[PDB]
Amino acid sequence: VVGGEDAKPGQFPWQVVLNGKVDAFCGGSIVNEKWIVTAAHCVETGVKITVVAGEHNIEETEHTEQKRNVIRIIPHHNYNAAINKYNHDIALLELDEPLVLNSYVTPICIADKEYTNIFLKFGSGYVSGWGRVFHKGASALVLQYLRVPLVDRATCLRSTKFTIYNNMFCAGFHEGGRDSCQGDSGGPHVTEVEGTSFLTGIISWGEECAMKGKYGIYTKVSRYVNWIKEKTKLT
Amino acid sequence: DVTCNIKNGRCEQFCKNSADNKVVCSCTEGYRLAENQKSCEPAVPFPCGRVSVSQ
Ligand SMILES: Cc1ncn(-c2ccc(C(=O)N[C@@H]3[C@H]4CC[C@@H]3N(c3ncc(Cl)c5c(N)noc35)C4)c(Cl)c2)n1
Ligand code: NA
């Protein structure tokens, strides 16, 4: 995240980090004690993934962290990386052993399809992650967060040469300087509803972080609510 | 003047239009609809989407 601020401990207790050959290569969000939602392009190669919940400073071993191994990866059934690495860019990760829910490890709420879309229409969400803090710059150590406004569709289409389908939205600032960045993909875009946060998007991609005239591109969660609820149901 | 399209029916989370120009509010998993018929109260120790650590 470029142009964000340090989270306080437990401010985004649904955030997770994904670690592999490099650390903090992507983010994710806690659906429940056994399931994480992320971007499918983060987990396409099927290589080993470590999920860390309750993380704050990725270079300090603290006490709220809960590390778990990923036992199964469920990319959305319509994801096909051979055609388009960023369409239907959403996946579910099953953990080996359940997270212990607490003030630092808390699920994100997921509304039905209609209300997830109403909440995105509020026009302002929060993104968070350990991605780069400048374009081509260093990764964050302390979790970063940023409020991003929804950008109208026509403005976003003109901002990029790549195609933006109706299952994606754009968010960010016309002046630049504030955006998601590489390493944040897969993390949450959430909308606060009277003090309860709901998942409205998955951080997906962009071309040049925080460059004036460019925006972050996100997956609309509303289209995938039913599939999340079905795949992650524990009862 | 009581519908889900006006101030969400005064529902904290979700609203459904019901008979006789009334609404029925509701909440996400882990919350209960409160006695005031509008608010959402935690019904589990660590309900989703809530910041509980002192900020
Ligand atoms: C056909 C298609 N549709 C999207 N495409 C595409 C094309 C180019 C890129 C790309 O190389 N983006 C660069 C590369 C380093 C910094 C930019 N980048 C980003 N990754 C993740 C994120 Cl979340 C962002 C962001 N908001 N701005 O830039 C981001 C990764 C990306 Cl991630 C996606 N290509
Ligand atoms: Na840490």
Image (cartoon, rainbow, N blue to C red):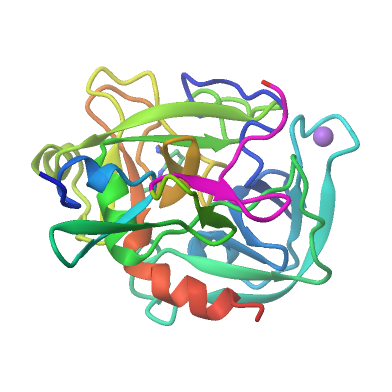
Q: Is residue B51 left or right of residue B4?
A: right
Tell me if residue A202 can be seen. Answer: no
Q: How many marks?
A: 0
- Tell me where residue A112 sits by quadrant: bottom left
Left or right, residue A211 beside residue A93 = left
User: In which quadrant of the rendered image does the C terminus of chain A lie?
Assistant: bottom right
- Seen at 83% across and 54% down, the residue is A67
* Residue ID at (17%, 67%): B19
Q: Give the answer, above or below, for where B25 lies relative to A125.
A: below
- The magenta-colored residue range is B38-54
Q: Position of residue A4 (x, y in %)?
A: 50, 21
The residue lying at 85 percent from left, 39 percent from top is A64
Quick check: A111 above or below B1? Answer: below
In percent of the image, x 63 and y 47: which residue is there?
A14
Specify whether residue A98 is in view: yes
Q: Is residue A94 left or right of residue A164?
A: right
| Relative depth, front residue between A114 and B31 | B31
Q: Quadrant of residue A98?
A: bottom right
The vertical placement of A49 against A9, above or below, is below
Work out whether residue B44 or residue A183 is closer to the camera in this orientation and state it: B44
Q: Main secondary structure of the magenta part?
A: loop
Q: List x then y, in percent, for residue A220.
A: 33, 56
Query: Residue B46 colored magenta?
Result: yes
| Residue A155 percent across, percent down from the top left | 12, 37
Residue A183: x percent and y percent? 57, 42
Residue A196 within the magenta-colored segment of the rendering: no
Quadrant in which ligand 1 is drawn: top left
